[PDB]
C-alpha cells in the first residue's frame, strides 16, 4: 500500500510535525477524506498505523449516536473513522437524516470555524450513500482520494507485513505467491495467512511452506 | 453435515488442548462461537458431546442466571467464575439466549437491563484485556439476530457464526437410532415417513417425543412400539 | 394376551397345543386389534404363520389404524413371509393409516426380492399416499439407488409431485446424491417443475451441481 500511504501522508502525516502553524499555513487544508472500495486493508491498519505514528488518540464510533458526538466535542483532536455506518424519503431516512445532520454540522463546525487545530477525520462509504452522500457533497471542500483494490506492488508489502508476524521459510518466492492471490482486496491475503495457520497447526510443522500458502490460495479462491 | 462438528472441533477443542500456542500458531481471537436457528433444538446434545469428548470443567449458565433484584451480584458471580476458570482449569462458559440481555435501551424504566448490559460492556472490555493467556472458552448460542447489539457482532469478538438448517435429516436419523438402539428393534418400524414428515412439521426434543411414545407403548398390550404411538405422539405434542 | 407371548417368543409346541386345544385363540385379538398373525409376522416366524395361514386366517385383517400384515412382511425383510402372504392373496395395494402402500415400506428395507414379488403381483408402481408421495421420494430420501432402479424395471414415473410440489429429483438433489440425480435425469427427470417455494432443482443443488444437471439434460 505504498501509493495509499503516499497519498495519505498529506492527510494524516501533515499535522504530525507542524501542529501549531496551521494558522500560518493558508493553503486551505481539506477537512476530511473518503476511501470507497472493499475494506480489505485501510480501515483499521492504515488509520491505526499512521495514527500510531502520529502518537495521538484514536477515537472510534463503533439513539446513542449523540453522546459519542459530545465526547468527540470534548476530545476534539483525534482521528475519527466511520466503521459501523458503512453498511425516496421515509421515517428511516429521517432517523438516518439525524446522522446526516450530524455530519452536516460536522461540516458546519469543521468547515464552519476551526475551534482547535489538528481537526482531521476520515470518511468511509461503500454503498448507495456514495451517490447520496456524493449528491449532498459536490466536491466543495473534500479530499478526493480514490481507494483501489491492492495491486501486486500493494500485495508484496502487505504480504511482508502480514508475513513477519508469523513463521516463514527461507525458500519462498514472494513474487509468484503474491501474483497468485487474486480476488477482492488485501483482506484475501489475510485470508491466505489466517486460513493457512490452521493448516500449519493441523500439519504439525514449525514453519510454513509455499505449498501450504498455495493450498490456502485454493481455499480462498473456492470461498470467493 | 460435519461442518459444525469440524469447525467447533478444530477451532474449539484443538486450541483448548494446547497451552500458550495462541501467539505461535498464527495469533487470532476466534474465542467467540455463535450459533443461530430457532427451529432447531440444539444446545443440549452439542453440549453433551463437548462434555464427553473433553474431560474438564464446564460453566453452564443460561443467560437469565443473573436476573435478580441484586444488580451488583452479576460482576461478583461472573468474576468468581472468571477467576476460578483462569485458576482451576480452562473451562467452557455456555452463554445462552443473549437476545434478552443484548438489546439496546434508551429510557430508564428498565434500568436493571441497562445496568446489566453495562456489566456486559464491562466484561466486554475485560475480555479485550484478557487477550493474553486466558484459561477459558466462551461459546454462545442465540435464537434472535434482529435486536442484537452491534458491539457483540463486531469482528475480533465473535469470529464464528454457525447456522442451523431447517431439515435436520441427519439429526433425525441419529436421534431415532440413538433411541431405537436401546429399545426393542421392530422390523415393522419405518423411518422414511418419520424422516420426511418432520421435514414439513419440524420441531424440537424429538428424543423426548420418542420417550413419550414409549410412555404410550408401556401399556404392556403392545410389546414393541410402532407407528401408532409415533404418529399419535406426534399429534399429541 | 397369552398368544402374544406365544407367537412373540416363538413357542412352537405351546402355540400348536394352544390352538389345537382352543381354536378360538387364533381369531382372538388384543386391545390394539392385533391378532397372532401380526405378532408372528412382526417377529418373523415362518412356521407359525404357515400354520395360521394353513388353517385359513384372513390375510386382510386390518388393525384399528389399517395396517395390513403385508406392510409387516414388506417392511420385515423376510422373503418367506411375503411368499406366504402373497401366496394367500394379500392386497398388494392395501390402504394403511397414512394411505401408504407396502411398496414404500418394502423400499424402506431395501429388499429387492420383496419389491419384485409385490410389483410382480400387480402392485401400482406410482402408488401415491395421502401426501402424494411415492416410494421414489423415500428411497431417494435414504439413498436406495438399486431400489429406485428395480422400480424403473417396471416403468415407474420419475416426476411425482409431492404435497409441497417436489419431484423425486428435488429430493434426490436435496439428499446430495450425485449418481442418483444423474440417473434420474438420464432416465427422464424434469428440471422445469417448481415447488410451492418457487425453487428449481438447479437452485436446490449446492456447489454448482445445477450446471452439470442441466449439462446432462442438454447432453
Image (spheres, grey):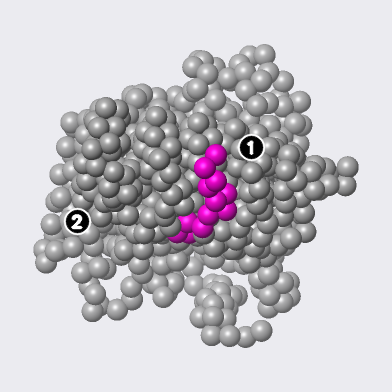
User: Is residue B60 at least partly visible in the picture?
Assistant: no
Residue A159 falls left or right of residue B93? right
Residue C146 percent coordinates (x, y): 65, 34
Q: Nearer the viewer, residue B171 or C26?
A: C26
Res. C41 image quadrant: top left
For this orientation, the residue located farthest to the right is C219
Q: In the image, which disc is placed on residue B201?
A: none
Find the magenta span and give its range: C87-98
Residue underneath mark 2: B65
Picture residue at 63% right of the left edge, 49% below the top? C123
Q: CA distance from mark 1 to mark 2?
A: 61 Å
For the residues carrying marks 1 and 2, which lies nearer the camera in this image? 1
* Residue C91 magenta: yes
What is the chain letter for disc 2?
A: B
Q: Is A64 situated above or below A49?
A: below
Residue underneath mark 1: C116
Q: Nearer the viewer, residue A12 or B210?
A: B210
What is the chain letter for disc 1?
A: C
Q: Nearer the viewer, residue A162 or C22?
A: C22
* Residue A168 magenta: no
Amino acid at each position: 500500500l505504498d501509493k495509499q500511504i503516499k497519498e495519505i501522508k498529506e492527510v494524516i502525516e501533515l499535522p504530525v510535525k507542524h501542529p501549531e502553524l496551521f494558522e500560518a499555513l493558508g493553503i486551505a487544508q481539506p477537512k476530511g477524506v473518503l476511501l470507497y472500495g472493499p475494506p480489505g486493508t485501510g480501515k483499521t491498519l492504515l488509520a491505526r498505523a499512521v495514527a500510531h505514528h502520529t502518537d495521538c488518540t484514536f477515537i472510534r464510533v463503533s439513539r446513542m449516536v449523540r453522546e459519542l458526538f459530545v465526547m468527540a466535542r470534548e476530545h476534539a483532536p483525534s482521528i475519527i473513522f466511520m466503521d459501523e455506518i458503512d453498511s425516496r424519503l421515509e421515517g428511516g431516512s429521517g432517523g438516518d437524516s439525524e446522522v446526516q445532520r450530524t455530519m452536516l454540522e460536522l461540516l458546519n463546525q469543521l468547515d464552519g470555524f476551526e475551534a482547535t487545530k489538528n481537526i482531521k477525520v476520515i470518511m468511509a462509504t461503500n454503498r448507495i450513500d456514495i451517490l447520496d452522500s456524493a449528491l449532498l457533497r459536490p466536491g466543495r471542500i473534500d479530499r478526493k482520494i480514490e481507494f483501489p483494490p491492492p495491486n501486486e506492488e500493494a500485495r508484496l508489502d502487505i504480504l511482508k507485513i502480514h508475513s513477519r508476524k508469523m513463521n516463514l521459510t527461507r525458500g519462498i518466492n514472494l513474487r509468484k505467491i503474491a501474483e497468485l492471490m487474486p480476488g477482492a482486496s488485501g483482506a484475501e491475503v489475510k485470508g491466505v495467512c489466517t486460513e493457512a495457520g490452521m493448516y500449519a497447526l493441523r500439519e504439525r510443522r514449525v514453519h510454513v511452506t509455499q505449498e501450504d500458502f498455495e493450498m490456502a490460495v485454493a481455499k480462498v479462491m473456492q470461498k470467493d | 453435515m460435519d461442518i459444525q462438528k469440524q469447525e467447533v472441533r478444530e477451532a474449539v477443542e484443538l486450541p483448548l488442548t494446547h497451552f500458550e500456542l495462541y501467539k505461535q500458531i498464527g495469533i487470532d481471537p476466534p474465542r467467540g462461537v455463535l450459533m443461530y436457528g430457532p427451529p432447531g433444538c440444539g444446545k443440549t446434545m452439542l453440549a453433551k458431546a463437548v462434555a464427553h469428548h473433553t474431560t474438564a470443567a464446564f460453566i453452564r449458565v443460561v443467560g437469565s442466571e443473573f436476573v435478580q433484584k441484586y444488580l451488583g451480584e452479576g460482576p461478583r458471580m461472573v468474576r468468581d467464575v472468571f477467576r476460578l476458570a483462569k485458576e482451576n482449569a480452562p473451562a467452557i462458559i455456555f452463554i445462552d439466549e443473549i437476545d434478552a440481555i443484548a438489546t439496546k435501551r434508551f429510557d430508564a424504566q428498565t434500568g436493571a437491563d441497562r445496568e446489566v448490559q453495562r456489566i456486559l460492556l464491562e466484561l466486554l472490555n475485560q475480555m479485550d484485556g484478557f487477550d493474553q493467556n486466558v484459561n477459558v472458552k466462551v461459546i454462545m448460542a442465540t435464537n434472535r439476530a434482529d435486536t442484537l447489539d452491534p458491539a457483540l457482532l463486531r469482528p475480533g469478538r465473535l469470529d464464528r457464526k454457525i447456522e442451523f438448517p431447517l431439515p435436520d435429516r441427519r439429526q433425525k436419523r441419529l436421534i431415532f437410532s440413538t433411541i431405537t438402539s436401546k429399545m426393542n428393534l421392530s422390523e415393522e418400524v419405518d423411518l422414511e415417513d418419520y424422516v420426511a414428515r418432520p421435514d414439513k412439521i419440524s420441531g424440537a426434543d424429538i428424543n423426548s417425543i420418542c420417550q413419550e411414545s414409549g410412555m404410550l407403548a408401556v401399556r404392556e398390550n403392545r410389546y414393541i412400539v410402532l407407528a401408532k404411538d409415533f404418529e399419535k405422539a406426534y399429534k399429541t405434542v | 394376551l397369552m398368544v402374544c407371548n406365544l407367537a412373540y417368543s416363538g413357542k412352537l409346541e405351546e402355540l400348536k397345543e394352544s390352538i389345537l386345544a382352543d381354536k378360538s385363540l387364533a381369531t382372538r385379538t388384543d386391545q390394539d386389534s392385533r391378532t397372532a398373525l401380526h405378532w408372528a409376522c412382526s417377529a418373523g416366524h415362518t412356521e407359525i404363520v404357515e400354520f395360521l395361514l394353513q388353517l385359513g386366517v384372513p390375510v386382510n385383517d386390518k388393525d384399528d389404524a389399517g395396517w395390513s400384515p403385508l406392510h409387516i412382511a414388506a417392511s420385515a425383510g423376510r422373503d418367506e413371509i411375503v411368499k406366504a402372504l402373497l401366496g394367500k392373496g394379500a392386497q398388494v395395494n392395501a390402504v394403511n393409516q397414512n394411505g401408504c402402500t407396502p411398496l414404500h415400506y418394502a423400499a424402506s428395507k431395501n429388499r429387492h426380492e420383496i419389491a419384485v414379488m409385490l410389483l410382480e403381483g400387480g402392485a401400482n408402481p406410482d402408488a401415491k399416499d395421502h401426501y402424494e408421495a411415492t416410494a421414489m421420494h423415500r428411497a431417494a430420501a435414504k439413498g436406495n439407488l438399486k431400489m429406485i432402479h428395480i422400480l424403473l424395471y417396471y416403468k415407474a414415473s420419475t416426476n411425482i409431485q409431492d404435497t409441497e410440489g417436489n419431484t423425486p429429483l428435488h429430493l434426490a438433489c436435496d439428499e446430495e446424491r450425485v449418481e442418483e440425480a444423474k440417473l434420474l435425469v438420464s432416465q427422464g427427470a424434469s428440471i422445469y417443475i417448481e415447488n410451492k417455494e418457487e425453487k428449481t432443482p438447479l437452485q436446490v443443488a449446492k456447489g454448482g451441481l445445477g450446471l452439470i444437471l442441466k449439462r446432462m439434460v442438454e447432453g
